[PDB]
Image (cartoon, rainbow, N blue to C red; front, side):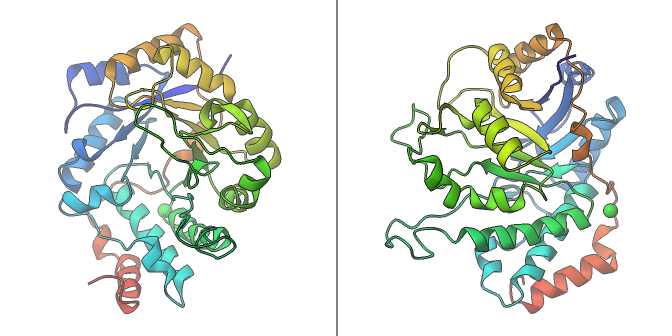
Length: 333
Ligand SMILES: [Cl-]
């Protein structure tokens, strides 16, 4: 049997009958929630519990979109950004505390994971080459992201690096085209690939960049066997879960339907295809997996969270100690 699975989304803050029906198919392995599905933690918790009454094996993910959810949805813990964490003598400890807090709360509201950490590099073109600003300090990024992952793992959560092989040097010439990073594989290896290389052995999963690196492969990274098999699983020895990029095309189009795109993604080596914001495309992709008679990738359940839903997480000693450490570092309050 070919292996693969579909991760989809829903429209609202609760399940429709149509939602319930699509979630029952075994080829659906995951559901991702966004700010549009989130009112507050207790609602998120009950939405997750309702999904698990249908499918206890479903992987439930939140795209917090760069601390996005925590900002306008009341009641989630506000955590410092990595650049604020970096400017401390105990930055590693603080990054651990942040990974631990985020993963503890996300699992307390019934989710398995948050897609984190970001491994993309910030390149200041205003600075000149060689400086840790134009290059983006990839070793420091890998150090602090590795600490953040330790915190996530300590709370029971599997970690997903994004966006492989790194989109920090990609340039969006316009709105229609897929961004490109036209540097050689040697240049990429010594810069944006570094955090992925450093952490491939620690990460449980990766998400690909929606970028063409035309000197390496003509295809976006999520569809390239050279990127996913030769470099990621081969050179980086990565044995974790590979998510596709979003198989719904709304900004940078590619040809074919979600059916051919999920086929191409699994062909390149993805374990789980994502179809967001497009239920019609999700049903086309599901139909494709049904005709392929796929079974779930043996890797997939690595992403299941070892924590669990609970309402008392914030009164626990570890939670208070973690916040007290961020407070002592002047990062919160
Ligand atoms: Cl745990």
